[PDB]
Amino acid sequence: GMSAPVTLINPFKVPADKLEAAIEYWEAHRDFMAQQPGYLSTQLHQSIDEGATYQLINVAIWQSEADFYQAAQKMRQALGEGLCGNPALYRVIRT
Amino acid sequence: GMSAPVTLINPFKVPADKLEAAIEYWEAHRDFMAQQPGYLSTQLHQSIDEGATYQLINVAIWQSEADFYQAAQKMRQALGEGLCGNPALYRVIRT
Ligand SMILES: [Cl-]
Ligand SMILES: [Cl-]
């Protein structure tokens, strides 16, 4: 197939009382990813209800699947309690 | 507090082999919500990997929390196997 822009959606389970630590962890990772070829933008969303399943959900845009996968492999090398993400790639199918 | 635009993020667990049915269910609901005061836009995202936890994730923008909650109460009245959402409201905190 041909490359096309993709969206990473990564919902996080944030431990009780550890939101700021989770944000700052996320920021360190964003700073690495933002330097990678194909990175376009991101929006880290915080739940209005602290009891939401996912108190943080990141939504990032990449130029292609290849660029994202290449960047994810590099981060395992560069950057390697209880914070749990579930990243997957998406495309928009309805509006 | 003062009202401000909010984002609904609703990740769906889609039963094996039932993606199209789930889309069409989602569309019927979108058609109701799109008529409600304060509805701004939506983007229904489909996973590139059929094995993702959430093969569909909707991301919708509403003018305020009040508008969304008002619309959600109305849909329970108007519209009432195994498809499971987890809606919550968010605001963007980092980019
Ligand atoms: Cl992320
Ligand atoms: Cl939805």
Image (cartoon, coloured by chain):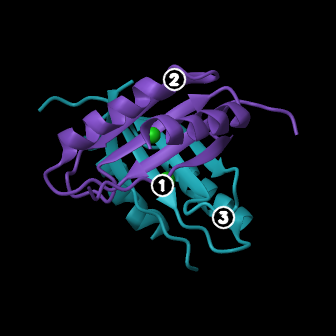
Chain colours: A purple, B cyan
Which of the image's four quarters has the C terminus of chain B? top left
From the image, tell me which residue sits under label 3. B51
From the image, tell me which residue sits under label 2. A41
Q: Which of marks 2 and 1 is nearer the N terminus?
A: 2
* Rendered residue at 67%/26% (across/down): A63
* Rendered residue at 62%/45% (across/down): A89
Which of the image's four quarters has the N terminus of chain B? top left
Q: Are marks 1 and 3 in contact (CB under 8 Å)?
A: no
**Residue B40 to residue B75: above or below:** above
B28 and B52: which is toward the camera: B52
Image coordinates for residue A57, horizontal then vertical, percent: 39, 44
Callout 2: 10 Å neighbours few (<14), some, many (20+)?
some
- Amino acid type of disc 3? Gly
Chain letter of disc 1? A
Chain letter of disc 3? B
Tell me the CA gap for discs 2 and 1: 19 Å
- Amino acid type of disc 2? Ser
Taking B65 as reference, is B55 left or right?
A: right
Tell me the CA gap for discs 2 and 3: 25 Å
Instruction: Give SS at disc 2.
Output: strand
Image coordinates for residue B26, horizontal then vertical, percent: 59, 58
Taking B61 as reference, is A46 left or right?
A: left
Q: Are marks 2 and 1 in contact (CB under 8 Å)?
A: no
From the image, tell me which residue sits under label 1. A86
* Rendered residue at 39%/66% (across/down): B77
Where is residue A52, by image quadrant?
bottom left
